[PDB]
Image 1 (cartoon, rainbow over the protein chains, first blue to last red):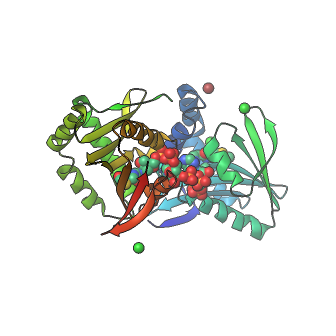
Image 2: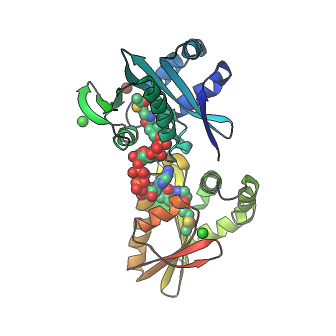
Image 3: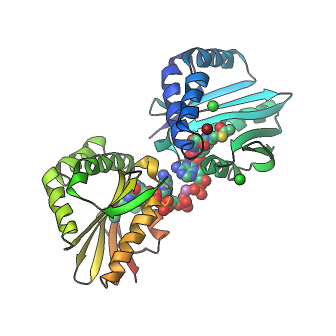
Length: 159
Length: 159
Ligand SMILES: CC(=O)SCCNC(=O)CCNC(=O)[C@H](O)C(C)(C)COP(=O)(O)OP(=O)(O)OC[C@H]1O[C@@H](n2cnc3c(N)ncnc32)[C@H](O)[C@@H]1OP(=O)(O)O
Ligand SMILES: CC(=O)SCCNC(=O)CCNC(=O)[C@H](O)C(C)(C)COP(=O)(O)OP(=O)(O)OC[C@H]1O[C@@H](n2cnc3c(N)ncnc32)[C@H](O)[C@@H]1OP(=O)(O)O
Ligand SMILES: [Br-]
Ligand SMILES: [Cl-]
Ligand SMILES: [Cl-]
Ligand SMILES: [Cl-]
Ligand code: NI
């Protein structure tokens, strides 16, 4: 199994929706209701909305939107925004059957390599407090909890 | 997520084949070709062979064959054989998406509970040496490597 990381493009659109869909249903099974999850996929992962985000990510050096490809098949992605020279990790999702093999770590490491060349010295993120899978992945990659906001924990890592 | 463990019945055969298929295709992906793995399902997990093993389990003879059910649907199994005073753990597999939530440990421990009642003082197993997933689970549950055989490590646990 060979993993390549690169900028997403519009040909990745349909497979990106399926990855998201599968990851959300699996990751949030004990956490959000079925309906919440389907509304979220239908709204946040519509063709039109994602297309616009993919195109934005293409021309904007302060938006990193990368896919993980396992033998040429898209199986995960990561989204980060840089504003005032600080990073926000907005999104990181793999297909469930591709978790626990450091592909997520690889996506994070590619992002941080780009942050490093830009001079970003801080990255924040929101993770749901019951998402033990995500939350523990971040604490194992140097993120610390600084605050809570509703049902999320706010985490930060310094560079 | 309500997990129930109980002996397999003939009713479970069809769903047992699909769990076997999917777990095996995932577990051995980096180790054997896709085609070889499929060939196993036709042969060792033929309808008839499995039925016979399910019935012997049901009849309380040399087979112990238990399933893990998530809200009434089969998502994993454990298969052991007893000979003389010893158990051999033949098979233990979950659907990939149901891994890493202690459902495997539940199966093992339910099996061990039935083994302690039958007086069995020793369990051995053969795990492919490149199967980190299985090997690490086993060493985290008291099993130790005693030997190798072909492509496998032989592990043992004493009661
Ligand atoms: C801002 C946000 O987007 S928050 C949402 C984060 N995304 C998710 O939770 C979606 C579902 N999960 C995933 O996509 C992935 O598991 C990620 C991205 C969170 C982590 O990537 P992975 O490549 O799976 O993790 P990686 O292999 O680098 O590290 C493994 C660690 O992550 C966690 N983890 C990864 N996969 C699993 C799994 N299947 N079951 C339980 N824990 C897991 C564990 O803490 C593990 O450490 P351990 O070995 O001590 O158990
Ligand atoms: C005798 C034989 O049949 S050998 C065949 C063994 N079976 C397999 O390898 C099939 C694929 N895997 C599975 O079906 C399951 O992972 C089992 C049956 C091996 C273990 O059951 P689970 O309920 O998943 O394990 P449980 O949650 O109790 O224990 C977790 C540990 O198992 C391992 N593990 C479980 N799931 C995963 C995963 N998705 N990725 C990597 N490691 C995993 C790790 O060692 C983990 O330890 P960690 O928390 O330090 O990472
Ligand atoms: Br909800
Ligand atoms: Cl999202
Ligand atoms: Cl809480
Ligand atoms: Cl070796
Ligand atoms: Ni783990």
